[PDB]
Amino acid sequence: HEKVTIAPLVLLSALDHYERTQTKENKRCVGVILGDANSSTIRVTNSFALPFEEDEKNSDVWFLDHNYIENMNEMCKKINAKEKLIGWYHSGPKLRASDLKINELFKKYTQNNPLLLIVDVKQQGVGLPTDAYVAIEQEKTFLHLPCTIEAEEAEEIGVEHLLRIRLTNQLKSLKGLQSKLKDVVEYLDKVIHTILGKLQDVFNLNNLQKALTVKTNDELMVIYISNLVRSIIAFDDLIENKIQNKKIQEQRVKD
Amino acid sequence: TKETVYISSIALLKMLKHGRAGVPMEVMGLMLGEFVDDYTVNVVDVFAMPQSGTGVSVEAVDDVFQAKMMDMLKQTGRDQMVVGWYHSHPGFGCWLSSVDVNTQKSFEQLNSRAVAVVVDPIQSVKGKVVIDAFRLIDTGALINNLEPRQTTSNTGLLNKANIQALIHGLNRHYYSLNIDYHKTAKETKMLMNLHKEQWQSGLKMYDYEEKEESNLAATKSMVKIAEQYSKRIEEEKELTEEELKTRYVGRQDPKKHLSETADETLENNIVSVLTAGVNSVAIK
Amino acid sequence: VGVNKDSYLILDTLPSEFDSRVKAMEVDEKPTETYSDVGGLDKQIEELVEAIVLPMKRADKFKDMGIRAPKG
Image (tube, rainbow over the protein chains, first blue to last red):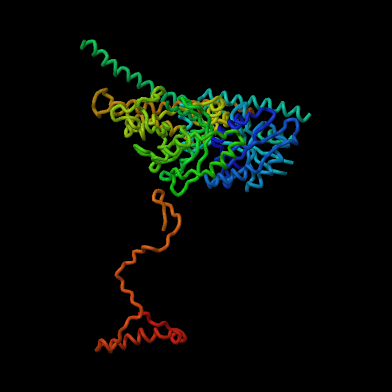
């Protein structure tokens, strides 16, 4: 597969455009992503929202203006010549006939496969308000791609000025197990096999583990060896304070 | 009175990124927003401007390009009046813009609220994020509206103010630089979920699991040799002063290996206890 | 070659104006002189006619032989 890296400036500007248009739940926002799709890792260096109109009760009602795309693309040529249209994003959790038919409309102005993005304006659950999705046919099949957040050197530093371990990983790991428990329940009521085929494949991945019991105690053996070094850390503080105590007793004498 | 500029998280990152190409190269852009004088000032959205043969100048503003953008920026409702311009220059002690001098005088005639912003660092930011703006006072600061009633003004004490080359007059006519940043409700939750210190999320279950227990291929591998490293670090400095007096002329030598091997051991124990602590339920 | 003063980037070439032509170079089209003005050099003048003047007249006669005429 491929990879997708989205800068935080793209997602920050995409959410405010939803507020600038005063779009309610009955409508969704659609926009275009710009970047370099030639490499294996798709990166979005620019984005802009489009005045997308849609009816929620009718999946056959959508409005997409292609005239603003041609003008905006010519205006970006005088800004950055390395920026081209790699695809288009959209808002809302649902994928309906409005978003599927417009996927081929942006394909005319996009050389490579347009990158599909579901943007969550309410930021509901976990992380990643926007997921990376690629369009492929065997019916439209949208496969998920790894979405990483990476910015430039001054971009990551500039955001830190705006905002200026063990238990953390455990609490985040337990939430993933709870999401899997509801994953098999919600899928079971939908059928009454493709996903279960991949699940049952990775489940199997003490006959051979009889010798694998010792490796647990081998790491615990080093922990006590580390605690021996960890104890030395405070053994010097045990010596360090007596370095003062000898000078402390020489104070009252001088007074 | 003067104006206090309030750049949000959206405008600061966009105006900066446009001027991050090259140390010597200079670019320019346009700021838009809707506010009133008498303190308050906002910036909605910005976009870069094309560079002419003169680089950054007053003639570099294209009325044809600017008119086409305001029509394209109307679709999302971000189209507003022109609140000023922002430029890019390497920066100096005084007059950071090597070209623009009186160009603001032609800008003040079009809009009295227009300013000229110049980014000094150009990818030199150490985390301070210091940017410079400009406003033409012309004849003022004598028997008129009192600017320094707001924040951080009446500077110029001795020879040291800001960069310390400006002192009192700053760039021209004491424009009284005031800059502040703010974050809305949407900008607060978005940035903290994207970039706060370092973004490890989306791996959250494997965050410290994959970076450590699954990275054991070569990370801490040969912990018996890793413990040997802590031995040589301690034995080196502990050998210095065993008499608790002045011999090798040192002070923090016993504390040098103390803090270094403490964080390493703390990481060695947490990763090791969480190897079987994840409880993948292997059974048989 | 036109380049930037700041970024030192090649933009467009320029026509030839100042080439550092090394002036005071004598350029004379078909001067007026005869070998009879300076005598006694007929021994060397003959060597100048054989190795220079005569092969300079017609190069097709020496080309049919396959050899190369001396250029100096």
